[PDB]
């Protein structure tokens, strides 16, 4: 799904020295005990905020949400509906298939490893910049919902992890 | 489908914006067989989207029968067809019309693009709203066969997504 | 009678495979018992509708109304006034000579066969298309009236029959 | 061009401009009265357009002419020109773009601002044709409840404009 | 399987206006209650006969027999043996694997959708013409047999449907 | 150019002009009522702009339409279009440039001078964008205390204009 292009701000510079910072952290681990929703804006992510707390500029080069199955999900698949939107749009709970590009993955079964449940962000349409001189309103936001399937409260059927690369530029001299 | 003659539209350079849309039609469990045939020109969600524009023509539409986790151990069968708005298929008889498909979603293969049915806008009519009321507008008709559902499992879900080009906004109520 | 030209819709295509379908059916048989009127739009004619019920496009190439006399009309001619109009205009009963091109035929007498009582349709001015993507409002409509001349209720002085050719294109896959 | 339109070949036909004007209705303040009409099938205009195959609006406007009886009692009517597809409800004509609320009468019977002209660049000028267009002009107006005397008729609504008629048909004389 | 070429009649014309008529109808629905055989010649198929009842010429351009599985066949596959022969050859019941090109499909199991159970007709070797000036004896004939696997008389394990395209030419003026 | 603006690359995107009109509020003379709203986050316009990423005003105006009940009792409202940064206080709308004092009703309900159009050459036309602009149009009007009957609603404030919407987003259908 390719969203139509929209006018965007122009940023001069982009020639300052900068380092690509690869980050990855498990978003959460989910079972089938209850349906659980989580929507997060990458501008205000706590771990990502503390990654770029000392730099003036920080823009994403790639980011993707990974729905990794576990062994306990071999005989009990679990369903997760996920979407990447702009920060302005805030999807509701369990209603991420109503937004264009929202996909409903089902992890488990005989195929315990597959790249069909990793949802990437189309940074050409979203806003790569997370921290800058001005606060942007169309930064990527990931919203997902996990449907209950009678889990036993501890098996942790699936794990949602988020990884990517953020380019950090222009450190500010504060301590 | 064989070609048919069609009317012509003059101004294709009018300011138009491509409007991607997606909305879940309904979630079905195999407790009872359920039919649904809808013309895209009169579907409630699409028409509340495009009631504010004078012209609205599709670029690509595709109905999707996405399996859920509960359908892993209990597949469900749906027969679907994309036809002309003049033709209204009956219940459970979507295989009697040319191009009708009989999808069966579920099982260990929980994800596959083989159950995605796209509309043939080359032969159908992309235009849903315009100066005239066409009769070749696409109609999607599907029937879900009962297989012993639990009335709460929601084995499958029906997702209709695509792109509609809207042009000439109207001074409507909102 | 040649009506002045009026602007008409433009239809692209017309290159799809199509078959000329020759049709002919007796419209009715009339005697002099009572004056009888009949006006019919060729778009909604039942026999013609079932001819083109499986095709997307159906346009006339020629059509004419034939007032054929019978033997019983040899010594008792009968009068029929007929007109071809657009579907918007609906002639009244026995008032088809007030519309431009309406003609009053008298069939019978020593000349029992003549082509002067066959009224053709000027499809250059009317709309040849009967079935298409859009419903047209100026398709041919034939309106005629039969005047009573003291018939004996069963002799069937004249027979009105309609024949023509309709080109059918773009079959639709329905059964 | 705001929106695409259906192609019409052979538009260079002999056509005549036909100015028309007719009073829509006279309204008093006894009760609120709504009226919405599509110019495609207006009863008192089709008689003008019955003799021709093509009718295309060049200009059209809705006029709210006050009467002298409205001097001591103003009357308010809300009107809008819209697409024939859109059918505004009663007293909701100010919620659509171009919808006005003409109040007439009052101390001075001179305000010539009661004209409500149709924006044919955002509408479909064609009223009659081979097909039945769905975006022809439609006028919708609602008259609010004044303290009317049930007989005064202290407001007048009229329609005037120009329609270009082409391709006459062999109709009744 | 490609049958060797055989001499065939020559037909002049083939330039008359003609429309491709796409047809599709479910042949039947079968379960495992009992073994059921069906052999049908496409020249005399009732639905196909009424499709081309008003045309002088009608020749196939493509046709295939589809063995579509159902949900109830997920845990209970069903076996169908099918063959396309000439109208002269009439296969017996449950003996379609003895004829060259006869294939034994098994529909069901974890793979509920596959194009390996759709058997097409080699119209280069068979006779595309179904209706013409003369009656041909080598028109396509489809013969299939469904083996019983202890079905419960109502589950309808599989559905056999037949779809194709027939070109219709030279309508005859009859009503 | 009155003042510098933020650069916006890729402005040649497919855009559609979206005329909008909605009645702001109906006011009686019972008590003085102030209302100042920024078009960047107006509740009844964001629903139009929620489905698109960029929204740029082409024209906008504030209209004070009198009602018939104002014939015998005029009502005065002071309004101004200003920078969203500036937030004029109550009854101080005539102290800013372009602030008008529309009095409506009176002997004649015909004065069409109640239009207050925004000067977009001195403002920021953009209502929605990647950033949150601080100089978008903001309309501020205060209605003074008449001798109202607390139910008459003898004045109406409406907003109409055109917004160019570009870059639709995959929002709800």
Image (cartoon, coloured by chain):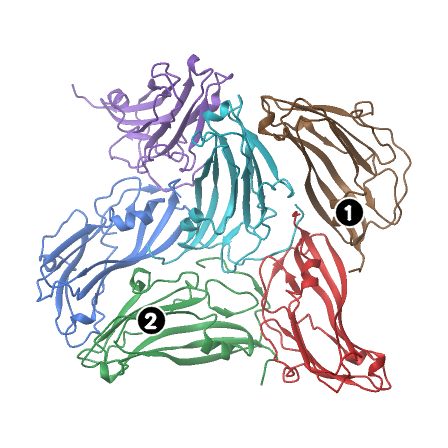
Chain colours: A purple, B cyan, C red, D green, E brown, F blue
Task: Give the quadrant of residue C61.
Answer: bottom right
Mark carried by residue F138 = none
Q: Are marks 2 and 1 in contact (CB under 8 Å)?
A: no
Quadrant in the picture for residue C26: bottom right
**How many residues crowd mark 1 within 10 Å: few (<14), some (14–19), many (20+)?**
some
Query: In the image, B98: left or right of D37?
Result: right
Rendering coords of residue F162 (x, y %): 32, 56
- Residue pointed to by mark 1: E49
The one of F165 and A26 positioned closer to us in this rendering: A26
* Residue B9 against residue D65 in the figure, above or below: above
> In front: A6, or C50?
C50
- Tell me if mark 2 has few (under 14), some (14-19) or many (20+) residues whose alpha carbon lies within 10 angstroms of its own: many
Q: Residue A22: tell me if it is visible.
A: no
Mark 2–mark 1 distance (CA, rounded to whole Å): 63 Å
| Mark 1 secondary-structure assignment | helix
Which residue sits furthest top? A71
Residue designated by label 2: D116
* Residue at 88% across, 45% down: E135
Residue C108, horizontal then vertical, whole percent: 82, 84
Question: Is disc 2 placed on a helix, strand or loop?
Answer: strand
The quarter in which the N terminus of chain C is drawn is bottom right
| Chain of the residue on which disc 2 is drawn | D
The reply to whether residue B101 is in sight is yes
Side (left or right) of F115 relative to C118: left
Question: Is residue A39 toward the left or the right of residue E129 in the image?
Answer: left
């Amino acid at each position: 799904p390719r969203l139509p292009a929209a006018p965007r701000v122009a940023e001069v510079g982009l020639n300052a020295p900068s380092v690509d910072y690869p980050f990855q952290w498990v978003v959460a681990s989910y079972d089938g005990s209850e349906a659980k929703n989580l929507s997060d804006d990458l501008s205000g992510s706590a771990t990502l905020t503390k990654v770029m707390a000392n730099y003036r500029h920080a823009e994403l080069t790639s980011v993707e949400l990974e729905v990794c199955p576990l062994a306990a999900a071999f005989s009990k698949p679990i369903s997760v509906s996920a979407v990447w939107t702009i920060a302005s749009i805030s999807p509701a709970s369990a209603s991420e298939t109503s937004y264009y590009g929202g996909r409903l993955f089902t992890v488990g079964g005989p195929v315990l490893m597959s790249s069909t449940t990793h949802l990437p962000a189309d940074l050409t349409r979203l806003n790569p910049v997370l921290k800058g001189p001005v606060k942007y309103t169309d930064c990527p936001r990931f919203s997902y919902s996990v449907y209950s399937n009678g889990g036993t409260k501890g098996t942790n059927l699936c794990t949602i992890i988020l990884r990517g690369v953020v380019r950090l530029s222009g450190p500010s001299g504060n301590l």
